[PDB]
């Protein structure tokens, strides 16, 4: 509904590069993806990742059932070929005739970063960037891109689940927190460069596995849905970074991505993947049970919900500012609001 | 919604006690149930059966995914603990802060009777009672509670199917009626104490199994959806009672309950259970086929439809009286209307 | 619904005679079918195929769960018996009482032809006929009725797929066309007696199987959805006829019928059936991908789309004429419009 | 085991012609079949149906995964081509070299008759013929070949089930016999030309469907597993022929064939197919329950079992005679033994 | 069993390191594997990969259902702890008593190499080594370990399929060879250091995909089941290495491993993985059809089968030498037999 239009102005991940390469035996795509209820197709056309509407201009077949040919995407039905700008450049049935002026499909800003493919549906405000991942190009850290995981929950509810200090004791007792560490601190939160920044020192000496990323937590949250969590672990005295971002596929579904990086990397990737998967399996049934899918005004917050409250407040401001136009939105997103004592 | 609001004032069964005990290994619940399209949770807190909306006040997680701890139902997400009145009495994240006054969920009338759990969503008219089961506390009779059975049919259509004299010869020829006995009598019907009361002396000497409850039929039907049928059986000269009641789960679904009692009880419970299941299997495809799900005004009645006609008329009066308020509803439900020669 | 009302005036196939005879052990039906989102029942009563709304006038049970009893269709619930005109002639519960005037269900035109059962929902314009199959009662030809095939695509899109000259090279390269023969001719198209008639000499010497019906193509397309394609095959110098017609089951679905006839018939029926199934398997994914299901005004045509363009034009004229009434519709359907040199 | 060797000398059906044509899109086969635990392949090579062992001489691949090429069967692995005599005639890898003398596979006598494909594994005694079907080439009769049906029972037990007069009342009460007609007559049985011949006049006026083939029964049973039953029906005064034969696939499995012919043929084939399928569904669970699969010496016969007793006696004689050689076997099979008063 | 005993003297791969790390959340195992019908367990104890019989000495529980605890493998039933030598070092029920001398399980050679785990069941001849992979520690090459693929075919038949020059034209026509290139050369074969070495210049200019490893083929085949194929590709003038090895799981099954390395590595791993999977899908049905599973003496060879013929000859020599003992086996395996012009 109208509520969601403002989200079209952000970059969202739609697939891993691995998913694109696996989709078709050519390794070039095409791959069908869905973002904010739009049916799109991604393909590697020459040196560029390209996103188009997954709908041929001729007779509305899905281009995602087609083939990459040179630097073009060829429709399966009558072979029309589309260039990187979504323009048809070949109509095989009519090689001599002029190509109709309207023989084109919409294309969208599309970039690879961190091993994911990102799409921005509306670029007209031109003030948003791909989220920040702190571990990129840090040679001290081994990076693992997990396979995406799908939840029957919204990106807003997923974000709040990831940053929620209060649930660890109840949803993750064997795994992330002691069940008796249920009272979290109230942390200062800064807005800077379109990111929420805040720091949380979790309890020490908790009976949790050594591969649990538990320690001093530094969050950099690129609004609206990306979370970069840098952990200085207590047990190993080493850096562990979690980068989690949700693709808002439609009104009730998320395709979620986790990339994690670690300084101590002589151990098995699957030690960590299995642990992450366990954490997600603990969250999933409870988060999918939340109803209605979008948080209504009747939910009852407590002081420990500060992160959730401030998140909802900023999202509300972004939605209102989007209605006022590009300049208002840019200010709402990028104006600093500092409440900690840190330098910037 | 509007057409069904009056049904919120009655007691409806939502599960058997056995279902509640089996739902969770604690034997205390919780169990998710649905009544009139409302999502509810049932649990046993101490000596009390409780029913609440299945939605935590904090972040809307389902309490039915939580845990009973003595006299509390604990939400699975952040561990809020609700007492028997639906009030949160512990917020683990803020154990010293005052609990918000809004931290409460709607609590509904919930009572065990006859081995079923009954819920009344609205008690404001204070004039409805749990349906009458004649065999309760008759020490002459052995009582068996069947597992519930789900039909893709409404409670009104199920009620009419149960009391329909004309269909026996076509739906139950091997089983309840001779295929020749298609013409039923037109019987007097009395309203008394919120019940329809009527008697039907079925045909004798029909080629049906001895466990068929066929004989003199005395109906006591607690409006809107319960039927107590006392059979003085021809074949065994002994009493057999069928108590059938439909939970209106939503606009197209019923969860149905059968409790039956018998005076001759030296035989197997499963002789009777299998017979009841055969009868229901004969009804099910035809009743599920009726469309639209609610009887529309264009259905064509004949004189043999008296029970159906009178039932529809009383339901319409109750709907209309509910709009006029508590006193009008009490009169529509509880005023006597006597057609027969009996006194009550 | 509103856009589709004009389609109710045509004869559409709903099942094969084989399907009707297999539906029930009596071989007389009843069989439930769906046409233009209407739920219907088909049965053979005496010598007549009948079609009625699949909904008893009494309590709305499905007559398709009932039984043919001589010259009657009997409802399963209370045994009301309907004659070939849809009128109830027996109410078993009240066999002496007058039958209500309202005890009737809607009866529709229903006729067997070519081994299919055809239904016309609206006969008020009295100007449509069952489509033309040229091989009927041609003793030189062996006729095979294939089993129906269901597609998640509309009847309009299926028709255009069948008559589309341009896609053969991309969808059927191994099978019907050389992949290099992508440029089709622009052929004259005649409207005559409610049929599109046109001829297409396909390319010779293509590397296609001997059982591929490739040759001189003569189309007689009974509007709106039936195609009679007479092929004078290059490879065998013999006649092969394809008759394809789509049942518009609802807004997203077709039940499609293929009947084929051949002059050289000493070979296996299954050589041809397997080839037809291969062609259909090649088309199915691409046609089911077209979205939205109904072609929007934004589709971009090229000159090679003449058949599709002219088809859409005639359908629009018929939809417009239907709003103006019976004589306007008759004119739009049956007036001749001749482009070619041929004489009719 | 050794018990079964004698069965290799008879013709057995292995598939319908329809199954062969459907197996491969060429309609020529190949089709894998199994007979007396031998893995065979059938193909149409030119004008001939050919059966070979399903095992290439080169590297033991299954020829049934190959292709018919001209009048040869081509192995899928390295393309060796086998002629109608099982001889390899092309080794693609070594076109100039002589083909090895041992490059051949066993072939077996293979013929089409009545729309089935028949194989005789051992032709060395040269005294057996394909079973007799009385309706072949009788233009008064419409013939229907049913799809094969598979049972977990032996061909001997299937034969005895088909000719058993005593079970109709218990396995087929609604369907073939009145439940009170349980006492059958003791009929004379003749051996003539390798066939058991006997006649049985079933009870009249039984409450069975009109499509039930009930009447005067004349059996011609080509030993060991084929039954030709000619029924002069009581209800319709018309001829109905049932031809049933079992393929002994292995020690515990049969692939069974039914062909039926009828003089009154204006009705639906599927009336009869559905009835036959119902009969088979009534027999199947009981016959599959018989254990051990081969009848042991401890079974207890009664006088009503005459047909079964005489069948087992003749099979025993054939098994013993096979051990004594070709002349003894020919006499055991073809010597007449007459006990009725009929002409031959 | 008897025929296969000699295979116990070689190193066979049983799982990838990835499979071991994924088996249990600890990433240390245990993992159940099967080799030559032996049930084994693999675990990482400290720095060592260990393999034991998967059967506790106490009450025969599977150790693969247990847990790694530091330098011990702990049985799930009564917690006996086994050291890297298969000796029990803790009996929790009797922690003071002497541990029985019989409280030990069989321990087998187990080593990681190339990302696979290798087991040698019998080390008594002390003359076999883990197979040679030429790309190991070649920094010019990117290495990809595929997931294992399981075939219902033996290791011998899989080896012959991989090195078979003749089948490419029939099994892989679109994919590896022109269908016309059916005649292979007869190449010299050298035995050196327990390897078969031979070179094959495949045909140039074939219509095969660019990612097809087609070019100059140099085989180094570590007996009995590992093949190292170095391809100097015609199409890219670059090195591509295929390392394929079969685990003989039991008498009918192989778990197969492919590792591939490539010099031009800027392209997608999944271009190559998809192509390898296509090749394997083309081979699988034909190789699984070969019967009996072990090649019998009756198979008929042609001159083009030189590689297969020489392979079977060497395997027979090794089986014969094994019966004569350690020094005979060492000689048969490691003595050089040079046919070519090359120098080693
Ligand atoms: C929210 N969240 C996670 O989701 C998570 C985690 N470690 C692993 N995961 C997967 N930590 C520490 C965490 O806070
Ligand atoms: C409606 N109804 C039943 O549903 C029924 C029954 N006996 C068993 N059942 C289950 N009888 C007598 C009956 O009238
Ligand atoms: C559209 N179409 C078909 O669908 C078809 C065909 N031959 C078989 N089929 C099934 N031909 C020639 C054809 O043009
Ligand atoms: C054994 N048998 C049948 O199996 C059968 C049948 N009619 C149909 N079937 C199928 N009859 C009359 C019969 O005797
Ligand atoms: C046997 N074989 C293969 O199995 C193969 C291959 N390339 C990929 N695969 C998988 N080549 C060239 C090959 O000869
Ligand atoms: S629908 Fe894409 S080319 Fe025609
Ligand atoms: S949602 Fe229930 S405690 Fe938070
Ligand atoms: S619903 Fe059809 S007879 Fe009653
Ligand atoms: S296995 Fe048949 S040709 Fe080689
Ligand atoms: S069976 Fe292993 S410790 Fe007992
Ligand atoms: Co969580
Ligand atoms: Co009923
Ligand atoms: Co097509
Ligand atoms: Co039988
Ligand atoms: Co191969």
Image (spheres, coloured by chain):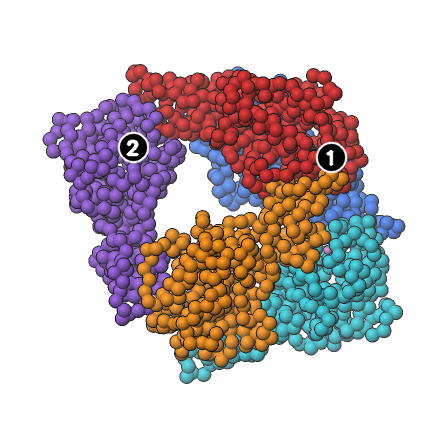
Chain colours: A orange, B purple, C red, D blue, E cyan
Q: Residue at x 41, y 53 (%)?
A: A293
Q: In the picture shown, does residue E240 fall above or below B107?
A: below
Report in which chain the residue with disc 2 lies. Answer: B
Within-10-Å neighbours for mark 1: few <14, some 14–19, many 20+: many
Q: Quadrant of the C terminus of chain C?
A: top right
Say whether mark 2 and mark 1 are on the same chain: no
Report in which chain the residue with disc 1 lies. Answer: C
Image quadrant in which you'd find residue D4? top right
Q: Is residue D296 rendered to the left or right of residue B336?
A: right
> In this orientation, which residue lies closer to the viewer: A51 or B285?
A51
Q: Is residue B69 rendered to the left or right of residue A22?
A: left
The residue tagged with tag 2: helix, strand or loop?
A: helix
Q: x%, y% of residue B319? A: 24, 36
Q: Which residue is mark 1?
A: C184
Q: In the picture shown, does residue C210 fall above or below C340?
A: below
Q: Residue at x 58, y 32 (%)?
A: C156
Q: Is residue B128 rendered to the left or right of residue A280?
A: left
Q: Residue furthest left?
A: B343
State whether residue D322 appears in this view: no
Q: Residue at x 73, y 69 (%)?
A: E222
> In this orientation, which residue lies closer to the viewer: C314 or E284?
C314
Q: In the picture shown, does residue C51 fall above or below A272?
A: above
Q: Which residue is mark 2?
A: B160
Q: Is residue D145 rendered to the left or right of residue B224?
A: right
């Amino acid at each position: 509904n109208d509520e969601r239009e403002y989200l079209r102005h952000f970059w969202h991940p739609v697939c891993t590069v691995t998913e694109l390469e696996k989709a078709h035996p050519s390794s070039l795509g095409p791959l069908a993806v869905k973002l904010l209820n739009e049916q799109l197709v991604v393909a590697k056309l020459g040196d560029e990742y390209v996103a188009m509407r997954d709908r041929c201009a001729h007779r509305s077949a899905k281009l995602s059932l087609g083939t990459v040919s040179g630097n073009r995407l060829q429709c399966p039905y009558h072979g029309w070929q589309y260039d990187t700008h979504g323009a048809c450049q070949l109509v095989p049935a009519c090689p001599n005739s002029p190509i109709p002026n309207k023989a084109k499909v919409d294309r969208f800003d599309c970039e690879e970063r961190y091993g994911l493919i990102w799409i921005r549906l509306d670029s007209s405000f031109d003030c948003t960037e791909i989220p920040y991942f702190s571990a990129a190009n840090d040679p001290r850290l081994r990076i693992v891109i997990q396979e995406p995981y799908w939840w029957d929950a919204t990106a807003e509810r997923r974000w709040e689940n990831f940053t929620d200090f209060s649930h660890f004791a109840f949803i993750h007792p064997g795994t992330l927190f002691d069940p008796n560490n249920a009272e979290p601190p109230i942390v200062p939160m800064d807005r800077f460069n379109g990111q929420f920044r805040f720091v949380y020192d979790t309890p020490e000496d908790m009976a949790v596995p050594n591969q649990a990323p538990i320690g001093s937590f530094s969050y950099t949250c690129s609004m609206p849905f990306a979370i970069n969590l840098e952990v200085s672990k207590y047990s190993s005295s080493s850096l562990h970074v979690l980068f989690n971002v949700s693709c808002p596929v439609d009104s009730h579904t998320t395709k979620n991505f986790l990339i994690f990086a670690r300084e101590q990397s002589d151990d098995s990737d699957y030690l960590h993947i299995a642990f992450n998967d366990l954490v997600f399996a603990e969250d999933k049934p409870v988060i999918e049970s939340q109803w209605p899918k979008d948080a209504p005004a009747d939910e009852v917050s407590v002081v420990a919900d500060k992160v959730s409250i401030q998140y909802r407040k900023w999202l509300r401001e972004l939605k209102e500012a989007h209605k006022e136009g590009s300049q208002a939105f840019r200010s709402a997103l990028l104006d600093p609001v500092i409440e900690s004592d840190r330098s910037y």
